[PDB]
Image: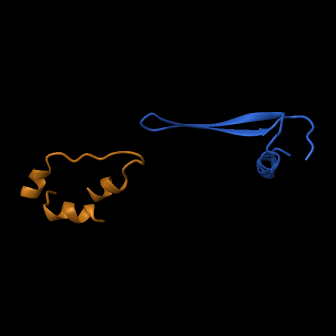
Amino acid sequence: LNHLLSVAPQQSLVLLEDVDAAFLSRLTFSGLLNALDG
Amino acid sequence: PARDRSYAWLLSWLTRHSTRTQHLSVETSYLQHESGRISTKFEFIPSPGNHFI
């Protein structure tokens, strides 16, 4: 997830739906938010 | 010569120093970025012939 979010194309939006599923629970809850702050 | 990179630099310097050049050519920078984003800009360059500065 961190690699995909870091290599996103320029001038492009990123959409992550169903964010509740990963947070409720490969799968991680704090890993995604840690990767976001990277 | 046109092969050397100083050609474009000298032409840009000329088109800046001599703002009122009656004879000139046009160079268009066109780039279509991904997601269909088009960037255009007109750079004006001295025309072939004789010019005095």
Q: Is residue A14 above or below residue A31?
A: above
**B44 sits to left or right of A19:** right
**A26 sits to left or right of B23:** left
How many marks are shown on the rendered structure? 0
Indicate how the structure is coloured in the image: by chain
Query: Is any part of residue B52 visible from this angle?
Result: yes
Q: Position of residue A35 (x, y in %)?
A: 25, 63
Residue reaching furthest left? A24
Q: Is residue A16 above or below residue A6?
A: above
Q: Position of residue A30 (x, y in %)?
A: 15, 64
Tell me the quarter of the picture where residue A34 sits.
bottom left
Residue at the spot 80% in from the left edge and 52% down from the top edge: B6
Q: Position of residue B20 (x, y in %)?
A: 81, 41
B21 or B34, nearer to the observer: B21
Residue reaching furthest front? B20
Residue at the spot 14% in from the left edge and 60% down from the top edge: A28
Q: Which chain is blue?
A: B
Residue at the spot 14% in from the left edge and 57% down from the top edge: A27
B20 or B12, nearer to the observer: B20
Q: Position of residue A20 (x, y in %)?
A: 10, 52
Q: In the rendered image of this protein, which colour is used for chain A?
A: orange
**A25 sits to left or right of A11:** left
Tell me the quarter of the picture where residue A38 sits.
bottom left
A31 or B19, nearer to the observer: B19
Query: Is any part of residue B3 visible from this angle?
Result: no
A9 or B11, nearer to the observer: B11
Q: Is residue B45 above or below residue A33?
A: above
